[PDB]
Length: 534
Ligand SMILES: *[C@@H]1O[C@H](CO)[C@@H](O)[C@H](O)[C@H]1NC(C)=O
Ligand SMILES: *[C@@H]1O[C@H](CO)[C@@H](O)[C@H](O)[C@H]1NC(C)=O
Image 1 (cartoon, rainbow, N blue to C red):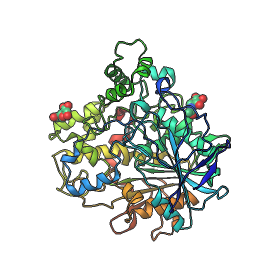
Image 2 (image 1 turned 60 degrees about the vertical axis):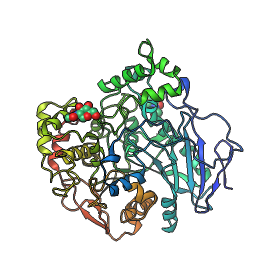
Image 3 (image 1 turned 135 degrees about the vertical axis):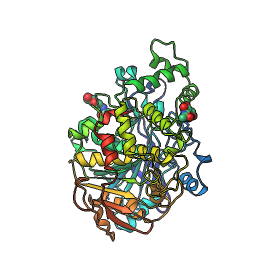
Image 4 (image 1 turned 90 degrees about the vertical axis):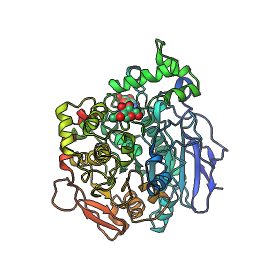
């Protein structure tokens, strides 16, 4: 059985899985229960000496997503969403969930000094666990290419438990507990990964969906100061679908509104101090109260109930303003998207069939947008069913007359043109961007949000060349191009550059292209980015 002795001298045992060795379920913070609820995580004080860490612990508490998709998707599309599992609640779950997991090449030991890939999971900041993202395909591929890596994944608090907001959270200085969980997991790696064979100065953080939005928050955290004990906590970042979070400050209208609603639902509506009251209620009361605020696949969709918000302390301002003001870590980044990011989210508003209904849906999801702004938005993404997402499928996939334009707006603001805005203002390091069209022709969803998880962790396809091989090459060497792929990946300087600046994936292989599509959407959306915050 593998062993490792932590920085403090505790010797722990892990698991020999033949194709790798796993140290699963190590606690890194005190259980955030009772009056530690919603507060910053506290370092685990306690001995792990003599203990065995052979299985994943429970995930943190999950919010029910509230989707209807399983009755509107064709069997082919549905089979693939079932597989990524990013839109499902994980089980088992517990408030005592803050554990970290280290998975390494067989025969690895202290002094091997391998690059470390730190994975951050993320379904809508409301669901997810580390147990649903198998490290074995990434590790087996790293060994095969002679660039072995260690895979570390960290649990963090999602939903009310991890991202409650409003005036009282703000006053107490407890905003964005979930991101602080991740950050403390990063410090733990800085202080203990050398004992497992890793090199703390070679950490690349990567994630997909809310986990990718998290990597962006970590680049902007403390105005871009990512150092811990005179060293950087990470040297590179990979963002699979997700850039800045389009959100109002922690004490803005919706953060407050969801707080009041949750406190009433938990039976704290008449408390003078609602946080004290919420730390008093039972785990079941808190879970039920949370499940009475909207889940991300409900009609509110990406007007998310729980998500990272600027607090003036650790995320000091509006994340678009921080990016154009240069307040970020200076690291090399890979950031990319699936071609049809918003189609899965489009299944939430399938009762919107007319333009007037569409106008009301945009006006209620974006409360800061003026009519003029909503008018420009609907001109940039017209009703014309050939111009929506799944992109370039003509008259196909139009579940409703508005499904494809709502899907185009959600995909772009949430993920695809938010990446372009970052790439056009980030000068912190070399930029590499990709866009996948691997699943072209898949009915209703196209190359949908989270399909990369299947080809990164379960199956091999043209996309695995980027999701495994290029990402291991980037983690090791800080250049994707050492993977030795058939196509050379172009460095991205800006969307207006001459020449191909995007690595692209189709059903058969890789090729390059340009990030110059839907410029009208990009100007409707990002001329004044606050107008479309939630
Ligand atoms: C948040 O910001 C303050 C400085 O404003 C700092 O003292 C604190 O440690 C930061 N928290 C984290 C988790 O980095
Ligand atoms: C669609 O359904 C939601 C509830 O699921 C409702 O609140 C909303 O107003 C409906 N919109 C239209 C245009 O029917």
